Structure formats: C-alpha cells, structure tokens
Amino acid sequence: DRLVINTQSFPNNYWDKFVKRKVMDKYGEFYGRDRISELLGMDKAALD
Amino acid sequence: MESHKHYTQSETEFLLSCAETDENETLDYEEFVKRFHEPAKDIGFNVA
Image 1: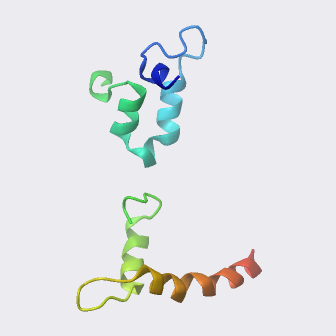
Image 2: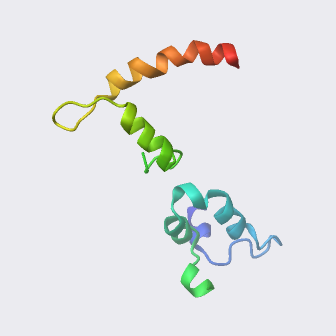
Image 3: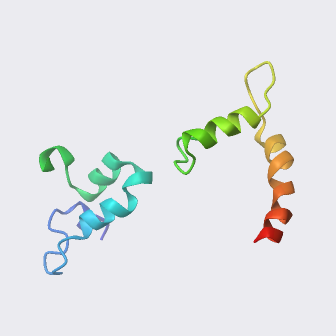
C-alpha cells in the first residue's frame, strides 16, 4: 500500500475523495509542503 | 532550530542569546542541556 498513495486515484471506491487535501492541511506545515505534495502525488502549480 | 520546525524565530534567537560559545563560534549541547533543562524539570512539574 506504499504505492496507493502515489496512485492518483486514491480512494476511488472509498467515497471520501477528499483525504489527500485533508492530509495536506494536517501535515503540510512541518514535513515540507512540496515533499508531502510529491509523496501524495499532487501538484500545487497545476492546481493553481 | 529551523529544521525542527517547532521553534519560531523568536525562540531560536533567544536560545542563541542564552547559549554560550567559545572562540570557535561553537557551543556544546551537553553543557547547554545540563545547565538549563534539568533545573526546569521539577519546578515545571510542580507548576503542572
């Protein structure tokens, strides 16, 4: 399951599609915004 | 100090000022901690 985090379709079946951003808010401040974003597979520049 | 990310700039600079260093612009954390952490332990426990 180390891989499913890098997978972009994280909880595809699980209806809370929202946990990537929840985790981003929870652990962004300490562990590095960019490092946590790359661990979770999402990209701030494309988001903006 | 800033890699720990629990310490703000004010706390970092206060610890810098309180810290004592030799001519090599270097400090010893063992001396620092034995000077300050252990004395605070029991008084802080009493306050708690």
